[PDB]
Length: 100
Length: 276
Length: 9
Image (cartoon, rainbow over all chains, first blue to last red; front, side, top):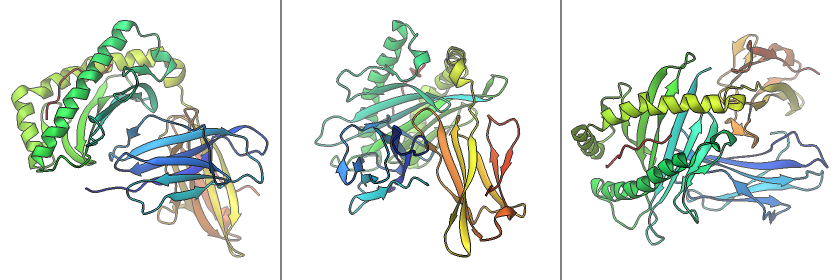
């Protein structure tokens, strides 16, 4: 049927400050149908402790979810979100940019 | 301000992988307060906000019964929808529903809602009169005739004007420290050169509740809608939301640009600029 | 408080 691909934002709960504990978020939205696979990556590797919100949807019926993990940002460590969905030929990886 | 209560249902078939999953979530404004998931180890209505925890066992039992019954009803609705669209039993399909009540600032019923979708497309909706239906296609007209015959709209009207409004007002009182508190955005403008002759100005709004906000850029006092990059409002994880709006401006023209913020938590609309 | 009305398609 008609399918919608996810939008992806990767960001922190609070302004990034190296050495200070924080939360790393991957917000996926705008997608249909609801099955979706989301991993958070720390230097390429899947973080094991990741929670997510309860499925809900927007007024246009598209779904959204927040995936989140506690993290302590540094200058060297790189974070990303990896998303798979039926609309994607291959998983999409969005790198965390502390200015966006 | 104004307030709303909404329930969101999603029922998802999955041939070969069991019976369809049914999930229900309840919100007051942008605050989730209950969830039910038929795939849980022990499916029951679960609290998602501190102010709902005080409800007594009669409350949890009534809502859990409703959601268990809905699980069965929407499994049958998914089977019926296959017949209405001549579809095979091999595919996965989704029914979604959102219903609830809006209050105005006085606290009276402003309007009620009960709208449903099939595979992410509008299917049927209760009209604003709470007495008639709008069907999106000839399958939903079959449903419409059934609900007209059963006077479903009269029952929904009684719920939307009665129990929905009464219990929304109750939750607003029990959760007044949070549900009736608007947190205004913390705002600032950042500056990022994109070249020797252009730079991005990004107007940030952080830490706000509820989610509704307007962020706009003006150049020489004229709205820059077409040239403005506006991200979707996003949850921070602590109940609050975030948003930004960005424009690419000629270097040396930054002070011709102003960012305008409207939010319920602000006594007056805010105007800000890049402060080097 | 959820609605108890049955919506049979």
